[PDB]
Picture 1 (cartoon, rainbow over the protein chains, first blue to last red):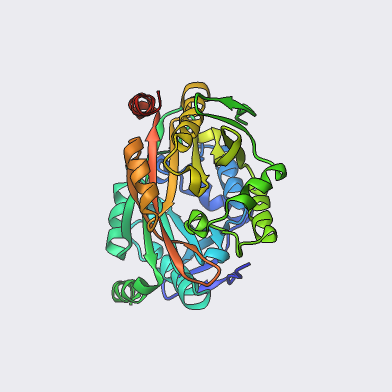
Picture 2 (picture 1 turned 135 degrees about the horizontal axis):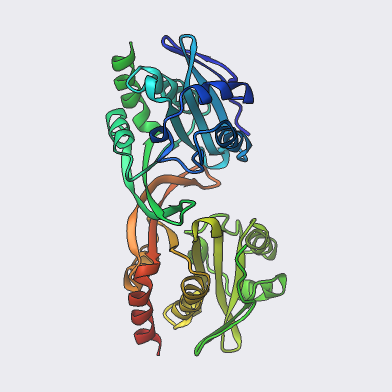
Length: 188
Length: 188
Protein backbone atom coordinates (compact mmCIF):
# COMPACT_ATOMS: atom_id res chain seq x y z
CA UNK A 1 0.00 0.00 0.00
CA UNK A 2 1.12 3.60 -0.57
CA UNK A 3 1.59 5.80 2.49
CA UNK A 4 0.72 9.49 2.30
CA UNK A 5 1.49 12.27 4.81
CA UNK A 6 -1.34 13.15 7.23
CA UNK A 7 -0.31 16.76 6.85
CA UNK A 8 1.16 19.01 4.16
CA UNK A 9 2.40 22.58 4.60
CA UNK A 10 2.31 24.93 1.60
CA UNK A 11 2.86 28.68 1.29
CA UNK A 12 -0.85 29.43 0.99
CA UNK A 13 -2.56 26.36 2.45
CA UNK A 14 -1.98 23.49 4.79
CA UNK A 15 -3.59 20.06 4.50
CA UNK A 16 -4.71 17.83 7.36
CA UNK A 17 -6.78 14.59 7.35
CA UNK A 18 -10.42 15.23 6.56
CA UNK A 19 -12.67 14.31 9.48
CA UNK A 20 -16.16 14.67 10.90
CA UNK A 21 -14.76 17.58 12.87
CA UNK A 22 -14.66 19.48 9.60
CA UNK A 23 -18.40 19.32 9.08
CA UNK A 24 -19.02 22.86 10.42
CA UNK A 25 -17.02 24.28 7.53
CA UNK A 26 -19.32 22.44 5.13
CA UNK A 27 -22.38 23.83 6.94
CA UNK A 28 -20.97 27.36 6.91
CA UNK A 29 -20.45 27.49 3.17
CA UNK A 30 -23.21 25.66 1.40
CA UNK A 31 -23.91 26.50 -2.24
CA UNK A 32 -25.46 23.91 -4.54
CA UNK A 33 -23.20 24.95 -7.40
CA UNK A 34 -20.23 23.64 -5.46
CA UNK A 35 -21.68 20.10 -5.47
CA UNK A 36 -23.70 19.97 -8.69
CA UNK A 37 -21.00 18.16 -10.66
CA UNK A 38 -20.11 15.73 -7.93
CA UNK A 39 -21.60 12.36 -7.27
CA UNK A 40 -23.60 11.87 -4.11
CA UNK A 41 -24.20 15.57 -3.78
CA UNK A 42 -25.89 16.72 -0.57
CA UNK A 43 -29.57 16.11 -1.24
CA UNK A 44 -30.65 19.22 0.69
CA UNK A 45 -29.14 22.42 2.21
CA UNK A 46 -29.22 20.80 5.64
CA UNK A 47 -26.85 19.47 8.23
CA UNK A 48 -28.14 15.96 7.74
CA UNK A 49 -27.57 16.01 3.98
CA UNK A 50 -24.11 17.53 4.31
CA UNK A 51 -23.17 15.08 7.08
CA UNK A 52 -24.21 12.22 4.75
CA UNK A 53 -22.07 13.65 1.95
CA UNK A 54 -19.01 14.02 4.21
CA UNK A 55 -19.50 10.54 5.71
CA UNK A 56 -19.64 9.27 2.12
CA UNK A 57 -16.26 10.79 1.34
CA UNK A 58 -14.70 9.34 4.47
CA UNK A 59 -16.17 5.90 3.90
CA UNK A 60 -15.22 5.17 0.31
CA UNK A 61 -12.80 2.23 0.27
CA UNK A 62 -9.24 3.22 -0.45
CA UNK A 63 -10.05 6.96 -0.55
CA UNK A 64 -7.67 9.28 1.35
CA UNK A 65 -9.07 12.77 2.08
CA UNK A 66 -7.58 15.99 3.37
CA UNK A 67 -9.17 19.23 4.44
CA UNK A 68 -7.50 22.25 2.77
CA UNK A 69 -6.90 25.04 5.29
CA UNK A 70 -6.55 28.51 3.87
CA UNK A 71 -5.82 30.95 6.64
CA UNK A 72 -8.31 30.41 9.48
CA UNK A 73 -10.81 28.66 7.26
CA UNK A 74 -11.35 25.23 5.82
CA UNK A 75 -11.49 26.02 2.08
CA UNK A 76 -12.47 22.60 0.87
CA UNK A 77 -11.01 19.15 0.41
CA UNK A 78 -8.69 17.18 -1.84
CA UNK A 79 -8.86 13.40 -2.31
CA UNK A 80 -6.71 10.55 -3.51
CA UNK A 81 -9.24 8.22 -5.13
CA UNK A 82 -8.74 4.56 -5.96
CA UNK A 83 -4.97 4.46 -5.52
CA UNK A 84 -3.51 1.38 -7.23
CA UNK A 85 0.17 0.97 -6.34
CA UNK A 86 0.34 -2.13 -8.51
CA UNK A 87 -0.32 0.00 -11.56
CA UNK A 88 1.48 3.08 -10.18
CA UNK A 89 -1.62 5.20 -10.59
CA UNK A 90 -4.28 7.10 -8.71
CA UNK A 91 -7.08 9.60 -9.26
CA UNK A 92 -7.11 13.06 -7.64
CA UNK A 93 -10.19 15.19 -7.05
CA UNK A 94 -10.81 18.48 -5.27
CA UNK A 95 -13.79 20.52 -4.13
CA UNK A 96 -13.47 24.07 -2.86
CA UNK A 97 -16.23 26.11 -1.23
CA UNK A 98 -17.42 29.05 -3.33
CA UNK A 99 -15.67 31.85 -1.39
CA UNK A 100 -12.32 30.28 -2.11
CA UNK A 101 -12.74 29.81 -5.85
CA UNK A 102 -9.95 31.69 -7.57
CA UNK A 103 -7.77 31.73 -4.43
CA UNK A 104 -4.48 29.76 -4.66
CA UNK A 105 -6.00 26.92 -2.59
CA UNK A 106 -6.97 24.49 -5.32
CA UNK A 107 -3.69 24.81 -7.18
CA UNK A 108 -1.48 24.48 -4.15
CA UNK A 109 -3.47 21.51 -2.81
CA UNK A 110 -2.94 19.77 -6.16
CA UNK A 111 0.72 20.81 -6.25
CA UNK A 112 1.35 19.24 -2.87
CA UNK A 113 -0.39 15.97 -3.67
CA UNK A 114 1.00 15.69 -7.22
CA UNK A 115 4.51 16.23 -5.90
CA UNK A 116 4.14 13.44 -3.37
CA UNK A 117 2.53 11.14 -5.92
CA UNK A 118 5.14 11.59 -8.64
CA UNK A 119 8.27 12.38 -6.70
CA UNK A 120 7.91 10.15 -3.65
CA UNK A 121 5.55 7.38 -4.62
CA UNK A 122 6.83 7.27 -8.23
CA UNK A 123 3.32 7.19 -9.67
CA UNK A 124 3.28 6.93 -13.46
CA UNK A 125 -0.26 8.24 -13.91
CA UNK A 126 -2.53 10.63 -12.05
CA UNK A 127 -6.00 10.97 -13.50
CA UNK A 128 -8.78 13.51 -12.97
CA UNK A 129 -12.41 13.02 -13.85
CA UNK A 130 -14.89 15.87 -14.26
CA UNK A 131 -18.46 16.29 -15.40
CA UNK A 132 -18.68 17.33 -19.04
CA UNK A 133 -20.93 20.13 -17.77
CA UNK A 134 -18.27 21.43 -15.32
CA UNK A 135 -16.65 24.00 -17.62
CA UNK A 136 -14.84 25.71 -14.75
CA UNK A 137 -12.95 22.60 -13.79
CA UNK A 138 -12.12 21.63 -17.35
CA UNK A 139 -10.57 25.06 -17.81
CA UNK A 140 -8.64 24.62 -14.56
CA UNK A 141 -7.22 21.26 -15.71
CA UNK A 142 -6.37 22.68 -19.13
CA UNK A 143 -4.46 25.44 -17.35
CA UNK A 144 -2.76 22.82 -15.19
CA UNK A 145 -1.58 21.07 -18.32
CA UNK A 146 -3.44 17.80 -17.83
CA UNK A 147 -4.17 15.94 -21.06
CA UNK A 148 -7.81 15.47 -22.04
CA UNK A 149 -8.03 11.80 -22.94
CA UNK A 150 -11.70 11.57 -23.74
CA UNK A 151 -15.28 11.47 -22.58
CA UNK A 152 -16.84 8.49 -20.87
CA UNK A 153 -20.39 8.89 -22.11
CA UNK A 154 -23.22 8.36 -19.59
CA UNK A 155 -20.66 7.25 -17.01
CA UNK A 156 -22.71 8.18 -13.93
CA UNK A 157 -26.36 8.24 -13.02
CA UNK A 158 -27.97 10.86 -10.76
CA UNK A 159 -30.70 10.23 -8.14
CA UNK A 160 -33.37 11.50 -10.54
CA UNK A 161 -32.17 8.98 -13.09
CA UNK A 162 -30.49 11.34 -15.52
CA UNK A 163 -27.02 10.45 -16.78
CA UNK A 164 -23.83 12.50 -16.87
CA UNK A 165 -20.69 12.23 -19.04
CA UNK A 166 -17.22 12.24 -17.44
CA UNK A 167 -14.22 13.90 -19.14
CA UNK A 168 -11.03 12.01 -18.24
CA UNK A 169 -7.72 13.87 -17.96
CA UNK A 170 -4.30 12.71 -16.88
CA UNK A 171 -0.79 13.82 -16.06
CA UNK A 172 1.94 11.24 -16.65
CA UNK A 173 5.19 11.16 -14.69
CA UNK A 174 7.07 12.42 -17.75
CA UNK A 175 4.73 15.38 -17.89
CA UNK A 176 5.02 16.26 -14.20
CA UNK A 177 8.08 18.52 -14.48
CA UNK A 178 6.25 20.73 -16.98
CA UNK A 179 3.11 20.78 -14.89
CA UNK A 180 5.12 21.49 -11.73
CA UNK A 181 6.80 24.43 -13.45
CA UNK A 182 3.50 26.01 -14.50
CA UNK A 183 2.09 25.54 -11.03
CA UNK A 184 5.13 27.02 -9.31
CA UNK A 185 5.10 30.05 -11.63
CA UNK A 186 1.44 30.64 -10.77
CA UNK A 187 1.80 30.00 -7.03
CA UNK A 188 5.20 31.33 -6.08
CA UNK B 1 -27.63 -6.40 -7.62
CA UNK B 2 -28.19 -7.45 -11.25
CA UNK B 3 -28.98 -11.10 -11.92
CA UNK B 4 -27.66 -12.75 -15.07
CA UNK B 5 -28.56 -16.16 -16.56
CA UNK B 6 -26.18 -19.03 -15.72
CA UNK B 7 -26.68 -20.26 -19.25
CA UNK B 8 -27.32 -18.77 -22.69
CA UNK B 9 -28.19 -20.67 -25.86
CA UNK B 10 -27.25 -19.14 -29.22
CA UNK B 11 -27.28 -20.55 -32.76
CA UNK B 12 -23.52 -21.08 -32.83
CA UNK B 13 -22.50 -21.14 -29.16
CA UNK B 14 -23.86 -21.78 -25.73
CA UNK B 15 -22.64 -20.11 -22.54
CA UNK B 16 -22.37 -21.72 -19.11
CA UNK B 17 -20.73 -20.44 -15.87
CA UNK B 18 -16.96 -20.48 -16.07
CA UNK B 19 -15.44 -22.87 -13.55
CA UNK B 20 -12.28 -24.70 -12.57
CA UNK B 21 -13.68 -27.62 -14.52
CA UNK B 22 -12.92 -25.62 -17.64
CA UNK B 23 -9.19 -25.54 -17.00
CA UNK B 24 -8.43 -28.43 -19.40
CA UNK B 25 -9.65 -26.32 -22.30
CA UNK B 26 -7.16 -23.64 -21.30
CA UNK B 27 -4.37 -26.23 -21.13
CA UNK B 28 -5.32 -27.68 -24.51
CA UNK B 29 -5.09 -24.40 -26.37
CA UNK B 30 -2.27 -22.32 -25.01
CA UNK B 31 -0.78 -19.61 -27.22
CA UNK B 32 0.86 -16.56 -25.65
CA UNK B 33 -0.66 -14.27 -28.26
CA UNK B 34 -4.09 -15.01 -26.83
CA UNK B 35 -3.09 -13.53 -23.45
CA UNK B 36 -0.51 -10.88 -24.37
CA UNK B 37 -2.97 -7.99 -24.16
CA UNK B 38 -4.66 -9.15 -21.00
CA UNK B 39 -3.73 -8.33 -17.47
CA UNK B 40 -2.45 -11.11 -15.26
CA UNK B 41 -1.49 -13.19 -18.24
CA UNK B 42 -0.33 -16.75 -17.51
CA UNK B 43 3.31 -16.31 -16.56
CA UNK B 44 4.35 -19.58 -18.23
CA UNK B 45 2.96 -22.23 -20.67
CA UNK B 46 2.19 -24.49 -17.72
CA UNK B 47 -0.78 -25.86 -15.87
CA UNK B 48 0.15 -23.95 -12.76
CA UNK B 49 0.34 -20.61 -14.57
CA UNK B 50 -2.92 -21.20 -16.43
CA UNK B 51 -4.66 -22.37 -13.24
CA UNK B 52 -3.53 -19.12 -11.55
CA UNK B 53 -4.91 -17.08 -14.46
CA UNK B 54 -8.28 -18.87 -14.38
CA UNK B 55 -8.51 -18.62 -10.58
CA UNK B 56 -7.82 -14.90 -11.02
CA UNK B 57 -10.79 -14.52 -13.34
CA UNK B 58 -13.08 -16.41 -10.99
CA UNK B 59 -11.94 -14.48 -7.94
CA UNK B 60 -12.26 -10.89 -9.07
CA UNK B 61 -14.95 -9.19 -6.97
CA UNK B 62 -18.17 -8.60 -8.86
CA UNK B 63 -16.92 -10.35 -12.02
CA UNK B 64 -19.33 -12.82 -13.68
CA UNK B 65 -17.70 -15.24 -16.15
CA UNK B 66 -19.02 -17.70 -18.69
CA UNK B 67 -17.29 -20.34 -20.75
CA UNK B 68 -18.23 -20.08 -24.46
CA UNK B 69 -18.98 -23.52 -25.92
CA UNK B 70 -18.64 -23.85 -29.65
CA UNK B 71 -19.60 -27.33 -30.71
CA UNK B 72 -17.79 -29.87 -28.51
CA UNK B 73 -15.13 -27.40 -27.47
CA UNK B 74 -14.73 -24.60 -24.99
CA UNK B 75 -13.77 -21.71 -27.30
CA UNK B 76 -12.99 -19.17 -24.64
CA UNK B 77 -14.73 -16.98 -22.10
CA UNK B 78 -16.79 -13.81 -21.81
CA UNK B 79 -16.97 -11.67 -18.67
CA UNK B 80 -19.17 -9.03 -17.12
CA UNK B 81 -16.67 -6.82 -15.29
CA UNK B 82 -17.42 -4.33 -12.54
CA UNK B 83 -21.20 -4.23 -12.99
CA UNK B 84 -22.65 -1.13 -11.33
CA UNK B 85 -26.46 -1.28 -11.29
CA UNK B 86 -26.56 2.09 -9.56
CA UNK B 87 -25.08 3.69 -12.64
CA UNK B 88 -26.74 1.26 -15.08
CA UNK B 89 -23.39 0.27 -16.53
CA UNK B 90 -20.94 -2.57 -16.85
CA UNK B 91 -17.81 -3.59 -18.74
CA UNK B 92 -17.69 -6.62 -21.05
CA UNK B 93 -14.55 -8.49 -22.07
CA UNK B 94 -13.90 -11.67 -24.05
CA UNK B 95 -10.98 -13.97 -24.76
CA UNK B 96 -11.12 -16.70 -27.37
CA UNK B 97 -8.51 -19.40 -27.91
CA UNK B 98 -6.59 -19.07 -31.18
CA UNK B 99 -8.34 -21.87 -33.13
CA UNK B 100 -11.65 -20.11 -32.72
CA UNK B 101 -10.58 -16.66 -33.87
CA UNK B 102 -12.74 -15.70 -36.81
CA UNK B 103 -15.46 -18.21 -35.89
CA UNK B 104 -18.85 -16.70 -34.90
CA UNK B 105 -18.11 -17.39 -31.21
CA UNK B 106 -16.92 -13.97 -30.09
CA UNK B 107 -19.72 -12.10 -31.82
CA UNK B 108 -22.50 -14.34 -30.63
CA UNK B 109 -21.17 -14.37 -27.05
CA UNK B 110 -21.25 -10.56 -27.10
CA UNK B 111 -24.66 -10.53 -28.76
CA UNK B 112 -26.12 -12.69 -26.02
CA UNK B 113 -24.65 -10.67 -23.17
CA UNK B 114 -25.35 -7.26 -24.75
CA UNK B 115 -28.97 -8.26 -25.32
CA UNK B 116 -29.42 -9.22 -21.69
CA UNK B 117 -27.64 -6.10 -20.48
CA UNK B 118 -29.59 -3.62 -22.58
CA UNK B 119 -32.93 -5.32 -23.03
CA UNK B 120 -33.43 -6.99 -19.66
CA UNK B 121 -31.27 -5.14 -17.19
CA UNK B 122 -31.83 -1.77 -18.93
CA UNK B 123 -28.15 -0.88 -18.83
CA UNK B 124 -27.40 2.56 -20.25
CA UNK B 125 -23.71 1.93 -20.91
CA UNK B 126 -21.58 -1.09 -21.75
CA UNK B 127 -17.88 -0.38 -22.01
CA UNK B 128 -14.97 -2.36 -23.47
CA UNK B 129 -11.32 -1.79 -22.72
CA UNK B 130 -8.50 -3.05 -24.92
CA UNK B 131 -4.75 -2.67 -25.10
CA UNK B 132 -3.70 0.02 -27.56
CA UNK B 133 -1.43 -2.67 -29.04
CA UNK B 134 -4.34 -5.11 -29.61
CA UNK B 135 -5.17 -4.10 -33.19
CA UNK B 136 -7.28 -7.20 -33.78
CA UNK B 137 -9.68 -6.36 -30.99
CA UNK B 138 -9.91 -2.69 -31.87
CA UNK B 139 -10.93 -3.70 -35.38
CA UNK B 140 -13.49 -6.13 -33.94
CA UNK B 141 -15.04 -3.38 -31.77
CA UNK B 142 -15.05 -0.94 -34.68
CA UNK B 143 -16.92 -3.56 -36.70
CA UNK B 144 -19.31 -4.04 -33.77
CA UNK B 145 -20.05 -0.34 -33.85
CA UNK B 146 -18.73 0.53 -30.40
CA UNK B 147 -17.61 4.15 -30.05
CA UNK B 148 -13.93 4.80 -29.37
CA UNK B 149 -13.97 7.27 -26.50
CA UNK B 150 -10.27 7.65 -25.94
CA UNK B 151 -7.02 6.26 -24.65
CA UNK B 152 -6.18 5.96 -20.98
CA UNK B 153 -2.44 6.43 -21.19
CA UNK B 154 -0.24 4.14 -19.07
CA UNK B 155 -3.36 2.70 -17.45
CA UNK B 156 -1.85 -0.68 -16.51
CA UNK B 157 1.54 -1.94 -15.46
CA UNK B 158 2.97 -5.33 -16.45
CA UNK B 159 5.06 -7.66 -14.22
CA UNK B 160 8.27 -6.46 -15.87
CA UNK B 161 7.30 -2.91 -15.01
CA UNK B 162 6.41 -1.68 -18.48
CA UNK B 163 3.17 0.26 -18.92
CA UNK B 164 0.32 -0.25 -21.38
CA UNK B 165 -2.35 2.15 -22.70
CA UNK B 166 -6.04 1.16 -22.69
CA UNK B 167 -8.43 2.23 -25.47
CA UNK B 168 -11.94 2.69 -24.03
CA UNK B 169 -15.00 1.97 -26.18
CA UNK B 170 -18.67 1.97 -25.36
CA UNK B 171 -22.12 1.15 -26.65
CA UNK B 172 -24.97 3.19 -25.18
CA UNK B 173 -28.52 1.89 -24.87
CA UNK B 174 -29.61 4.21 -27.69
CA UNK B 175 -26.95 2.68 -29.89
CA UNK B 176 -27.85 -0.93 -29.10
CA UNK B 177 -30.51 -1.37 -31.79
CA UNK B 178 -27.98 -0.44 -34.48
CA UNK B 179 -25.32 -2.66 -32.99
CA UNK B 180 -27.81 -5.52 -32.62
CA UNK B 181 -28.76 -5.19 -36.27
CA UNK B 182 -25.16 -5.39 -37.48
CA UNK B 183 -24.52 -8.38 -35.27
CA UNK B 184 -27.63 -10.22 -36.40
CA UNK B 185 -26.80 -9.60 -40.07
CA UNK B 186 -23.33 -11.06 -39.51
CA UNK B 187 -24.48 -14.00 -37.37
CA UNK B 188 -27.82 -15.05 -38.78
